[PDB]
Image (cartoon, protein in one colour):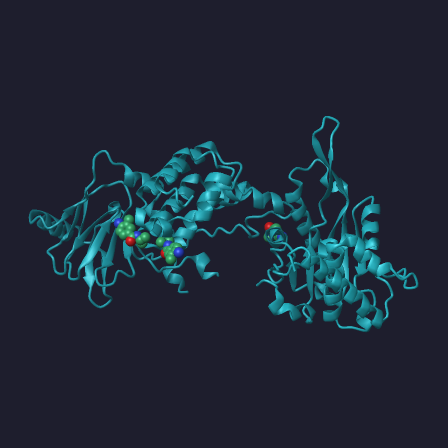
Length: 237
Length: 300
Ligand SMILES: Cc1cc(C(=O)NC(C)C)ccc1N
Ligand SMILES: Cc1cc(C(=O)NC(C)C)ccc1N
Ligand SMILES: Cc1cc(C(=O)NC(C)C)ccc1N
């Protein structure tokens, strides 16, 4: 069924699974026209497809040309997401194909179920977790590749850097979700926390800075304070 | 005008013959139903006074043979049978009529209700949905499941309605995943009408039979089929005008006949609200929308 706090360790077992988040697929800026009406201008987007056990991120960049001349773009964006996820699973060797795909928004269920009808053995599941993957475009290297794209492109990343050499995938996912939740709640402050000390750098082949184990504890504490401090000032506690 | 005699009525039972019903007391001298209109299918139907559970009955067409009812005390139900001896049958019937031991099919002359509910229903198609080839009539009861229900357990006792499934390979073309799911016209017109049913009359006949099974026996799986066949049309942007007009008439008479106190278990809120207010055909069912709004506005 649905994925929630009760079955959270299932994410880190040995059954291949992918989260799919569609919240950055169709992105627009809203602006005034010369006549004083409102119009939208699309900007490049991305599908966020993540294996939470390994950190492997399949970032399919959605170039604005895909929207040209199309209607009902927010509806189309869900179907385009499902088309691209189906294409990805079909590009993978059978032994790498997921046994479950967890969608972060329930509106993706029927689109994904229709593209993957012929795969009756891949479970398409929703979740009750409120995961912060929308904040992926606050990761500078991810935002950069999306905005620079001049055509459709798939780019592969490991969203955990080398963390799995030292920590488990449960702990890595928890760190990732903490970082993203912070970036979502207060992007400027979160980014200040991550880059305050110039001596800690981001390797060319990494997304996040090269924190020692002790520095990660400090970082994580700073981020937990950002989230709780912003939650307590918002819900009057 | 044809006749279905009863050998006797040993157990107290409510007997139906299409929309009409009457109560027969234990061992009451009831010997059948006369003046049954020729030209239509009919359904006789029963509910034991002691066990309102398992309402059951028989679809038949008197043009296809001489049929009668006889209670079986072993299997505990009223069974339809065919009498092959035409002279024995004529003699039985003429005697029961002389003794006035039969109820008359009570059709009002103005009244087209049964025709309107069975316009496209043919015995030959009933017998393909309900497979028991040794009889010319077809038994149905409240508990019988459908083929599609069995896929989600005795196949001989199943309702073989045409399986409709909106998230299936049959309903969706590869490369038209979104198009076919949001506009079911190719599934309706090519897969089902041209491919499976051959014409809209056969489609409407199955839809009407599903409704009647749902309304007369509470066959849940019949109800699922009726709503699925409505939704398939309403969710198609391209439907022949004559089919939409006939569907509006079909559904109008179904809603009109539907007994008020079973509305909650015979009408699916989601399907009807979607069909009347959101679908491509939201503005094409004027008669049905008017009767629904005046008879069951709660559901909407
Ligand atoms: C939507 C969808 C349709 C089909 C389909 O109709 N296949 C038939 C040729 C057997 C296959 C896969 C799929 N994802
Ligand atoms: C129209 C009609 C319906 C019923 C009835 O019990 N229907 C439920 C199964 C929903 C009984 C007699 C009758 N003449
Ligand atoms: C209890 C309950 C029963 C039925 C049911 O048997 N319906 C048949 C008459 C079609 C339907 C819905 C429901 N909630």
